[PDB]
Length: 344
Image (cartoon, rainbow, N blue to C red; front, top):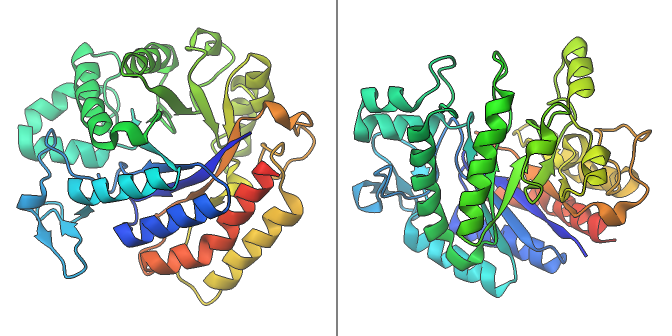
């Protein structure tokens, strides 16, 4: 009995409350149970915030009801809008899982902090070594993160039993892994005290250190190797990182986010709608819950009872010329397929 749903990247491409509710309808009617809301990344922080001072009252509202931060020029969901989505989700039995990504994938947060609190403040929270990451070793940085987590927790309230702490694609130019264990553990126990379970991307789970991780942290496992196109890098990561079966063997809750079958990156083109349709059929024909390592079937899990669930991820990077509703209508078949194939 599985945890299954949608990860929706609203940081790279914005979606109206109406369209978000349509995604919820699909999840619900297909027998799924969560919406993982990826609202914070480099390009935007897509919800209202007291702490980052992104307020509906400060915004320009479009005819479509969508609030635009006049400094960043980017959209965000108001608290009233989020309360409307929360009520709708809750009545449909769909859990909302917020994702506040760190230590990387957080430039929009930096940019809001800089504007409101100033550049010297912001630089003090950053890694001295890499300019695109929070300093996971700085107590003050941890305190700051936790203050924003508290706000996000307050916003989603009882619609959420899990909070996603991100943890993807960080430290690529540096050695930072040991301190990541410490950082992620601190975040998980802070959430635990708030009555929340932790979700996290698999990227930082390596053989050398993974046994130090809070074994209650729940893993969203997307790729063995970060989908690197460099084959020497792919080989190092596969030797260093933990596999999905290795995690299962240690007792972890793991959801299969397999980027080969379960990531879609919508892009307007003459074949977008056909391609999306085909993706659904491809998952139906060729994907099953035990297939975790991209398209590779040699290491598949035969005992799928151990795999906690799966999600379709709709990523926003390439979707600039597409409307939210076009994306939603065209990915419906694929989202249904992933949910049904996961639940059986």
